[PDB]
Structures are given as C-alpha cells and as structure tokens.
C-alpha cells in the first residue's frame, strides 16, 4: 500500500473491507501517507463499527 | 524514499552520495521498488567503491 499510494490519490475513495481488519488497515494506510485523505473515506454503517 | 518512488521515475538518474552509506541506501531503494532502475544508476569511480 506504500507503493499503492500513487493509485489512491482521489478526492473521494470508496472503501469496502472488514472492520475487524480495518482497525489495522486504516492505521497502515495512515502510515502509508494517506492520513490527510484518511478522514475522507466511505463505509456503510453496516460495514462500519 | 518509499513515498519518493513517484519522483524517481526516470530512464537515467544521477546519484551522488557516500559509498559507505550507499550500501545501506541502495538496498533501501531496492526495497522501495526501484530495483529495476537499480541497475541504471550513475556514480563516478571516485564515488564508487
């Protein structure tokens, strides 16, 4: 995902993952360099915790 | 440098560093994703080992 920072440069990004995995994955993506877009991510409330 | 992979996409790149540091730095750049360009790097023989 550190290599995939180049392909995640969007004003709005759709995200559909497992929320149990996503507490690890979102911190990984914040350490990738996507913290400024980390507030601009979409989940449904069922996918959300 | 993992973030700086995007700004090192050139057919030929000039490199001027310390060769004592460069045995660490070049392996770092290979783990960044620049191994395919790792054979296309320039040093003088004085900068080289």
Image (cartoon, coloured by chain):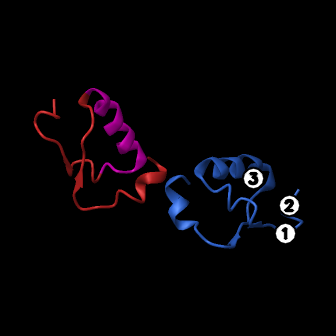
Chain colours: A blue, B red
Q: Which residue is mark 3?
A: A22
Earlier along the polypeptide chain: callout 1 or callout 3? Answer: 3
- Mark 3 to mark 2: distance in Å? 9 Å
Residue B31, relative to residue A11: is it above or below? Answer: above
Question: Going 73% across and 60% down the picture, which residue do you hit?
Answer: A17
Residue A28, placed above or below residue A41: above
Of A39 and B46, nearer the camera is B46
In this figure, which residue is indicated by the disc labeled 2? A48
Q: Is residue B24 magenta?
A: yes
The residue carrying mark 1 is A44
Whether pointer 2 and pointer 1 mark residues with C-beta atoms closer than 8 Å, the reply is yes
Chain at numbered mark 3: A
Q: Chain of mark 1?
A: A
Q: Secondary structure at mark 1?
A: loop
Residue B43 is situated, as x and y percent measured from the top left of the image, at 17, 42
A23 horizontally vs B46: left or right: right
């Amino acid at each position: 995902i550190q290599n995939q920072l180049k392909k995640l440069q969007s004003p709005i990004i759709l995200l559909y993952c497992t929320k149990e995995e996503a507490t690890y994955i979102f911190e990984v993506a914040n350490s990738v360099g996507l913290t400024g877009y980390g507030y601009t991510w979409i989940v449904p409330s069922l996918v959300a915790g």
